[PDB]
Image: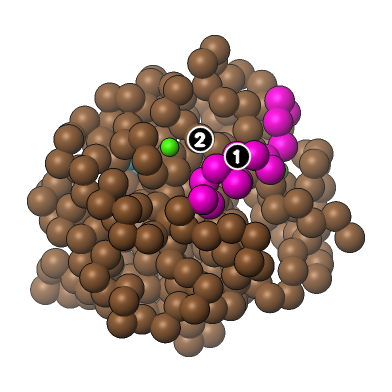
Amino acid sequence: AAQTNAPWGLARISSTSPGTSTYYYDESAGQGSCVYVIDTGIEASHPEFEGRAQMVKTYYYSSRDGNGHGTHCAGTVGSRTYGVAKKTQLFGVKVLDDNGSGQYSTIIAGMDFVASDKNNRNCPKGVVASLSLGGGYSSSVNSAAARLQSSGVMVAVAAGNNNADARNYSPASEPSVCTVGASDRYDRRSSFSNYGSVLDIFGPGTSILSTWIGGSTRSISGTSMATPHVAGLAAYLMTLGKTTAASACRYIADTANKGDLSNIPFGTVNLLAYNNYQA
Amino acid sequence: VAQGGAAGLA
Ligand SMILES: [Ca+2]
Ligand SMILES: [Ca+2]
């Protein structure tokens, strides 16, 4: 299958060179896998989700996305036009408020909620977690993401939008999750993207067009537009049978395009997520 | 982290 006129980072994920505009992927499109988007929430009623998106938990009075941010991230994962995994199942966990912030204890609780929730969710192909969230270094926050990965969930996390080493940022520095940095249109690390030996992979994170609240769309930048790209690549790859929650990050790095990125600091991997689908 | 589109982990 081929999506013609696809957002840049989708096409970049199915190509070995930059400047392409078509997105290539298997028509299975991540059916049978489920992705939990921990965040501001998800506008489940967005027609781009086609009844495949759903609010599963809030730590607030409202289970809705009154920010937009969560919706944007969930759209790069699985919306129909903007999504990597166009048929995956999306679950919303609101650990961030409408401004887009949350305390550590509530985001640790939301990670632990998925650990248990996934057992009673029909995801035959596997379960992934997308965390476009983070802050100062926390050993409880790293511990919680380690348990989540350990429960059999492919955990993808943002590197941090600081242009410094991701080692001083909370879930990012957890060595066992899949830590995602951002790249731009021209195959350069995004200027704001963190780096460090803790990163595993880079995804498109600059000028990423996706779904927004109010049944609309919006284009924004950050390690947060990059995370869900590798989160949807896992779900798609897992639904292909190529890998599973435990091995997924390793498999994505081992099959990434190598040495394509410029502006990559020494000690940081030069790997860009790739779906390996030539037609 | 959150609000409007952006990203985090730092
Ligand atoms: Ca890692
Ligand atoms: Ca690529």
A96 sits left or right of A235 in the view: left
Q: Nearer the viewer, residue A38 or A186?
A: A38
> In the rendered structure, which amino acid carries the disc numbered 1?
Ala
| Residue at mark 1 | A253
Determine the residue positioned at 81% across, 39% down. Answer: A17
Q: Position of residue A105 (x, y in %)?
A: 10, 51
Res A32 seen here: yes
Question: Label 2: how many residues lie within 10 Å, few (<14), some (14-19) or many (20+)?
Answer: many
Determine the residue positioned at 74% across, 64% down. Answer: A25
Query: Badges 1 and 2: C-beta atoms under 8 Å apart?
Result: yes
Determine the residue positioned at 70% across, 31% down. Answer: A258
Label 2 CB less than 8 angstroms from ligand 1:
yes
Pick out the residue farthest to the right. Answer: A279
Pick out the residue farthest to the bottom. Answer: A51
Q: Position of residue A167 (x, y in %)?
A: 33, 25
| Residue at mark 2 | A200
Q: Earlier in the sequence, mark 1 or mark 2?
A: 2
Stretch in magenta: A247-260
| Image quarter in which the N terminus of chain A is found | bottom right
Q: Ligand 1 is found in which quarter of the picture?
A: top left
Q: Is residue A249 magenta?
A: yes
> In the rendered structure, which amino acid carries the disc numbered 2?
Asp
Q: Secondary structure at mark 2?
A: loop
Q: CA distance from mark 1 to mark 2?
A: 7 Å
